[PDB]
Amino acid sequence: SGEADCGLRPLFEKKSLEDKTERELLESYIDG
Amino acid sequence: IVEGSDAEIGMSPWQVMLFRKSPQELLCGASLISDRWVLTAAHCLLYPPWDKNFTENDLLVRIGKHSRTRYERNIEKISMLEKIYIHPRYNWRENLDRDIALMKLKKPVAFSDYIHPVCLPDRETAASLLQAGYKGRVTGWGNLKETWTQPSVLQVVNLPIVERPVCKDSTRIRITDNMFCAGYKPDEGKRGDACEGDSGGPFVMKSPFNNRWYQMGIVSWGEGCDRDGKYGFYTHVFRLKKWIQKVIDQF
DNA sequence: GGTTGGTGTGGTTGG
Ligand SMILES: *[PH](O)(O)OCCCOc1cccc2c(OCCCOP(=O)(O)OCCCOc3cccc4c(O)cccc34)cccc12
Ligand SMILES: *C[C@@](*)(O)[C@H](CCCNC(N)=[NH2+])NC(=O)[C@@H]1CCCN1C(=O)[C@H](N)Cc1ccccc1
Ligand SMILES: [K+]
Ligand code: NA
Image (spheres, rainbow over the protein chains, first blue to last red):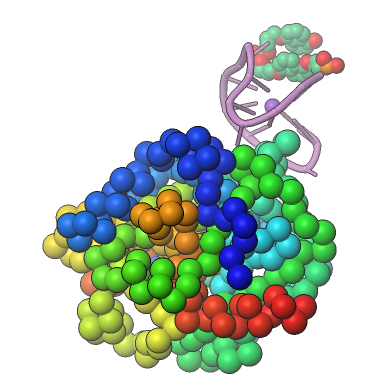
């Protein structure tokens, strides 16, 4: 029963901008 | 948060502060999951051993905050609780099994650049993301160091999930299916952990399918803070998701 | 100061 717009940050996703250390999160998925 | 860094403005817009009304003390973390509902660790509200049994009128909840102490004028929004719902089968006696609690707010909070709700995972998302070696994110205003050895702004740290084998043989405390640990192994070079005053604080991962953020964990317990061989434990949000929906729709 | 630190052509915000 997820909320319509949840999990999308106004100052990041909503502006196609990435935070300082979110790439680290993605790397984990690949060579983790 | 131990060995983390200062968050960026709006990095974690679902991050919520449980604030004690009398006196003024930071209690715990929490996360905003709608405009009316907030999620936290149950041991933040009800832990008899420490003589903690708070109720709606003991606590307000602060949203949109970054600075730990200052009232961020024109940024933060303060809300009062309508009701609290500690999980029925919450075992505070033994091992904090089912360390989860919901809170409805009197009036719905408005969303801004600093206030936005997080998503709860589902069958598929939990299956995909919640796997060993896969890193999540922890945020809180808790202690920078272990008790026997506090930040000025919200602290963030990225921490890899750990397999139950290594997760169970780490502690003498009985584990359940409603938990998972996270943190670096002693050889892994990088280190870091949640600490005291981080409970309720969300453990989030970012879906690489839809670029949405999902709250996979709640900060529950530890054994010191960031010591080799020890890992922080988190409430498994999905395995309790059935309970969460129940509570919302009924109330 | 303030429901709030430190130092402002604010800042994540007035005055
Ligand atoms: P609105 O526009 O209706 O009303 C807002 C106007 C009120 O302005 C201020 C009131 C109080 C404080 C400040 C302020 O504080 C900054 C403190 C740190 O700077 P400092 O300690 O170095 O002080 C600056 C040095 C010069 O001092 C003064 C300058 C002008 C007037 C006075 C005064 O009347 C008494 C004492 C010192 C000074 C920053 C800006 C505005 C206000
Ligand atoms: C309430 C939270 O602030 C806090 C978070 C723990 C952070 N630790 C790390 N490094 N991950 N939780 C606690 O302090 C919990 C609540 C009750 C006691 N407790 C502990 O962490 C104990 N040290 C361990 C424990 C005791 C009894 C039952 C389960 C665990
Ligand atoms: K000011
Ligand atoms: Na550790």
